[PDB]
Image (cartoon, rainbow, N blue to C red):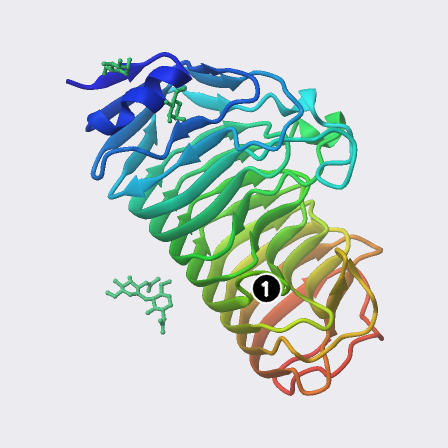
Amino acid sequence: STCTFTSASEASESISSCSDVVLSSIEVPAGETLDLSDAADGSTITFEGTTSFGYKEWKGPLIRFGGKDLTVTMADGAVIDGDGSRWWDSKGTNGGKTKPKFMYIHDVEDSTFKGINIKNTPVQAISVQATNVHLNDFTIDNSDGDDNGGHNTDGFDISESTGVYISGATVKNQDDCIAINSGESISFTGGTCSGGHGLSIGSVGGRDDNTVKNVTISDSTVSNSANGVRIKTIYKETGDVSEITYSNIQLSGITDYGIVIEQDYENGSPTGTPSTGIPITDVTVDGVTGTLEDDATQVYILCGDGSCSDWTWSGVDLSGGKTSDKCENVPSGASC
Ligand SMILES: *[C@@H]1O[C@H](CO)[C@@H](O[C@@H]2O[C@H](CO)[C@@H](O)[C@H](O)[C@H]2NC(C)=O)[C@H](O)[C@H]1NC(C)=O
Ligand SMILES: *[C@H]1O[C@H](CO)[C@@H](O)[C@H](O)[C@@H]1O
Ligand SMILES: *[C@H]1O[C@H](CO)[C@@H](O)[C@H](O)[C@@H]1O
């Protein structure tokens, strides 16, 4: 007795009483969240047809998950379409129109999301605040944003999580493919990132949680993006970044930085001066290869005095771009 919902109200009202849920071409009203947070433990949720959202300049989120032992999937041909170009104005979260957050995978545990297919989010696509979740074969296609004013269209923003396993994601966007602001035991593998800002740890600091530990980013590609591999920490803040592994990352058409690790962020931009309250230790880089554009820098490491240590750097083989003469306090295991 699968429950089939054709409206947001039906879902919100009835989801908790259902073990098998079908969300059939829901047109979510403007200014409302498609609220699935009261989903029954152990239930299955399937998206069918096109899920859409009415236009309002508000903060979202457009979709909110919640619960335990969930299985979330998409029917053949199904898509969750944010139709973000309605909001896009080249300013994203920094100005212009108020733009809603898209998908919150918050207050979720021991659940698997499979084949989630998303197009044109207003700003950031997925906010993850979860425990022991698998996010498999996602497609987050914000490629329309390149010519239609997309900005801050992050793939996965991760914070306050433990055990988040992303596999097989494809992210076409205008900002970070993934951004880990905090978390423990986070992995991203078999990913295809294009258009944006790369595979990022940070910015780290100034939040409720400023600890990143045990991150593995591997077997993935990053194309036509500002950065390949990145770790950013905030000037004069505290936290800890450790046990980070980048393995078998292939880059193409990188425009800014192949690998960039810097401890000098303030107000969303580099100051040029690092600080030492957010140590970055036990970082392994093993096999980062590919191509950089003419004005890109291969490697830029801007660490505080003593605040980056115990790095294991090998197989860094980049072609094109420039060599930095601005690196500071580079760990013995590494090189610009
Ligand atoms: C770092 O993260 C990995 C997960 O990315 C943790 O290892 C796993 O633990 C269970 C134990 O059976 C395995 O089934 C999983 O397959 C493991 N995951 C992976 C990707 O290998 C690992 O223990 C963490 N390291 C710590 C906490 O020291
Ligand atoms: C989802 O929406 C329903 C009605 O739309 C509420 O009753 C429920 O609390 C949740 O907000
Ligand atoms: C949600 O759906 C259930 C049926 O599964 C209804 O009983 C309820 O009133 C709401 O429509």
The type of residue carrying mark 1 is Val
Q: How crowded is mark 1: few (under 14 residues within 10 Å), some or many (20 or more)?
A: many
Q: Position of residue 153 (x, y in %)?
A: 64, 38
Task: Give the residue drawn at x 51%, y 28%.
Answer: 62
- Please provide percent x and percent y for residue 29: 51, 15
In the figure, 132 relative to 240: above or below? above
Kindly tell me whether residue 75 is visible in this rendering. Answer: no
| Placement of 240 over or under 118, stated as above or below | below
Q: Which residue is drawn at 57% across and 22% down?
A: 31
Which is nearer the eye, 180 or 58?
58
Quarter where residue 298 is shown: bottom right
99 lies left or right of 135: right
Q: In which quarter of the image is residue 43?
A: top left
The image position of residue 249, as x and y in percent, is: 55, 58
* Helix, strand or loop at mark 1: strand
On the picture, is 80 further left or further right than 295?
left
Instruction: Using the image as rendered, state which of residue 146 and residue 242 is in the foreground.
Output: 242
Residue 53, compared with residue 160, is above or below; it is: above
- Residue 62 visible? The answer is yes
Q: For this view, does 101 lie left or right of residue 6?
A: right
Q: Position of residue 184 (x, y in %)?
A: 43, 64
Residue at the image position 52 percent from the left and 61 percent from the top: 182
Q: Mark 1 points at which residue?
A: 288
Which residue is nearer to you in this view: 137 or 61? Answer: 61
Quarter holding the N terminus is top left
Locate the C terminus by quadrant: bottom right
Q: Give the left or right position of residue 123, taking residue 182 as reference.
A: right
Residue found at x 36% / y 35%: 37
